[PDB]
Every structure is written in C-alpha cells, then in structure tokens.
Image (cartoon, rainbow, N blue to C red):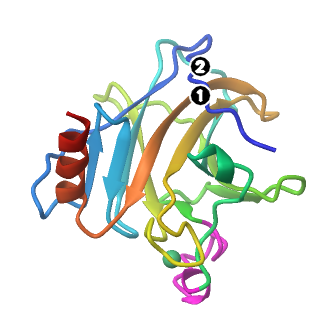
Amino acid sequence: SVPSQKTYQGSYGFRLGFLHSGTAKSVTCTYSPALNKLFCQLAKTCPVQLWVDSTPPPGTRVRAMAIYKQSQHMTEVVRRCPHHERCSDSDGLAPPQHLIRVEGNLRAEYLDDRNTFRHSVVVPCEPPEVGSDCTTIHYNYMCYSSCMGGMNRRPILTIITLEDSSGNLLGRDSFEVRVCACPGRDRRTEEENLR
Ligand SMILES: [Zn+2]
C-alpha cells in the first residue's frame, strides 16, 4: 500500500548527491541538506547524482517514484493534476499523467504499476563518463506542489531505488521535493523557519 522510504546503502554503497546551486532568486533548482529537500521550478532540469563505492552488476537500474510525505495521504497515488495531465506537453515517452520524467535518456521506461497504480520512471545504471566520479540523472517535475486537484499543496518525497535486473532492491535513498515558482526564496524561508 505504501513504498518504503528507508535509506539503505546496500552492498554497493549507494547514495545520492546534489549540486550546490545557491539561493539566488533566479535559481531554478536548489537542494537543502538541512531539510533534505529539493526546491525546483516546473519542468526544469533537476540534476541528481548517483554515487557508489563499488560497481553494481550489468543490468542494474535506477528507479524514481514520488509518494506523499504525510502519512494520512501516503496511500494516494501522486500524479499530475487535472490541468497538467491534459496540456499535451508530452516528450514522446512519458505518459501525460506522470509527475516525474527523466530528461535526455532514450532508455528511460515509464511504469504504471498494475497492482498499486503508482507511477515510476526507471533507467539503466550507467558508470560515470571518463574523468567523472559519479553519474548524474536529470529529472523534471511536471506539476507545482500547489496544483489544485493534484498535489494540492501537500509535500511529496521522491524515492530513488537501485534495483537488479528483476527489480529487487539493491539500495535506496530519498528526498523531499517542493515544485514552486521561486526555489531560492522558498529554500531560504524554510531554512530560516527550521533555524
Ligand atoms: Zn499541475
């Protein structure tokens, strides 16, 4: 009924990494370590790094799924709102109902779970380019946290799972996400509230 969100590095020492983009009002995507929360604009590139201590087997994949953060909403499938699922902004691969898309990866697969009805996007786990120490996936969130009839101001978490070729768990990490008009200002505000 509810996907696990327990951090698990697993045998390969799997964990996420985020850039340090700052909080200028112009920033389009910014991550707060103190809040473990990514703030981003609608449909803008969200670079998420994948780090491992050892190389996982050929066929390993990386899946992203969103769930509501509040327990009383956790059984509800996170999906795009009645407006955005109908705006015909398809990239040719992602179903119009899916909140999370992967940018620039023709091998991305989108799943509508036949039992839970939850949405997810999965890609092959690739090694870093020569000269790099990690691999980066570029995600896009396709609705604002405030969209009526959809997330409707409810906070969500994105769960990233490292899986084997059968879909079995190898590792897991997660972070809260707020899709908003001014990520820099909102990150500053929430960090101040926390302080
Ligand atoms: Zn929307």
Q: Is residue 145 left or right of residue 66?
A: left
Q: Which residue is mark 2?
A: 8
Q: Main secondary structure of the magenta part?
A: loop
x then y, percent, for residue 190? 25, 47
Seen at 49% across and 69% down, the residue is 142
Seen at 63% across and 70% down, the residue is 93
Query: What whole-number distance in Å separates the C-alpha atoms at marks 2 and 1?
Result: 5 Å
- Residue 164: in magenta span: no
Q: Is residue 132 above or below residue 114?
A: above
Quadrant of image for the C terminus? top left
Q: How many residues crowd around disc 2 within 10 Å: few (fewer than 14), some, or many (20 or more)?
A: some
Quick check: marks 2 and 1 in contact, CB under 8 Å?
yes
Residue 27 sits in quarter: bottom left
N-term-proximal mark, 2 vs 1: 2
Q: Is residue 183 above or below residue 128?
A: below
Q: Which residue is mark 1?
A: 172
Q: Which amino acid does the dot numbered 1 rest on? A: Arg
Residue ranking furthest to the right:
115
Q: Is residue 116 above or below residue 5?
A: below
Q: Which contiguous range is marked in magenta?
A: 83-98
x then y, percent, for residue 150? 58, 72
Q: Nearer the viewer, residue 80 or 63?
A: 80
Q: Is residue 64 above or below residue 154?
A: above
